[PDB]
């Protein structure tokens, strides 16, 4: 049964997850990609996205992507780098 979106009275996904076109919560491209209804910027962060911080304690890379790798947390990291 739909848990988010227009078919769920406008409910948003917990932990900032993306709501797919069909009303389900997730973080893969099938949820955040084409057709995404809400909280679709889950993987983006930083100055290009209103200064948004990543969920799950992920680092925000210099290019505005959320992750845990050295490339996300090292040189240029914008937030939650350690
Ligand atoms: Ca941390």
Image: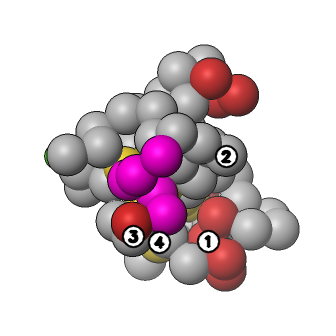
Of the pair 73 and 9, the residue shown nearer to us: 73
**What residue does disc 2 label?**
63
Disc 1 versus disc 3: nearer the observer: 3
**What residue does disc 3 label?**
69
Type of secondary structure dominating the magenta stretch? helix
Q: Quadrant of the N terminus?
A: bottom left
Of the pair 72 and 2, the residue shown nearer to us: 72
Q: Is residue 81 magenta?
A: no
**What residue does disc 4 label?**
26
Residue 57 is situated, as x and y percent measured from the top left of the image, at 23, 50
**What residue does disc 1 label?**
31
Looking at the rendered structure, the number of numbered marks drawn on it comes to 4
Q: Is residue 27 visible?
A: yes
Q: Residue furthest right?
A: 34
Q: SS for tag 1?
A: helix
Please give the range of residues in magenta: 71-75
**Residue 39 lies in quadrant:** top right
Q: Is residue 30 above or below residue 78?
A: below
CB within 8 Å, label 4 to label 1: yes
């Amino acid at each position: 049964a739909p848990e988010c979106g227009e078919r769920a009275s406008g409910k948003r996904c917990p932990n900032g997850k993306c709501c797919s076109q069909w009303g389900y919560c997730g973080t893969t491209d099938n949820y955040c990609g084409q057709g995404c209804q809400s909280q679709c910027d889950y993987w983006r962060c930083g100055r290009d996205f209103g200064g948004r911080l990543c969920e799950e304690d992920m680092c925000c890379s210099k290019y505005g992507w959320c992750g845990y790798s050295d490339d996300h947390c090292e040189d240029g990291c914008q937030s939650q780098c350690d």
